[PDB]
Length: 123
Image (cartoon, rainbow, N blue to C red):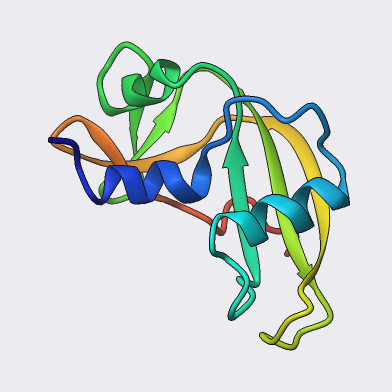
């Protein structure tokens, strides 16, 4: 059962609810989702309902975007953890960046499997 890619999607881009959304939340969760040895340079988590996400995969909450990317109709609460310093080696210090924006993903068999991680950057 399940999609090992979607659960890879879930594993690193989803967190139902964070009682906190600061830098210490970022340095905690990233480490706890096996994202620190090495340190991911930038990672974004999505909060809230898990189905308002699978919906992006279909018309009810998602519109075609760029090449194969789909973009959501509803905006989402998000926490972007930007590595700090540059060394891929721990300790990995992050700076969170909470926002309210729509996510852009890639679906496979109606399930999100990829996250366009660059839209969440600061050019």
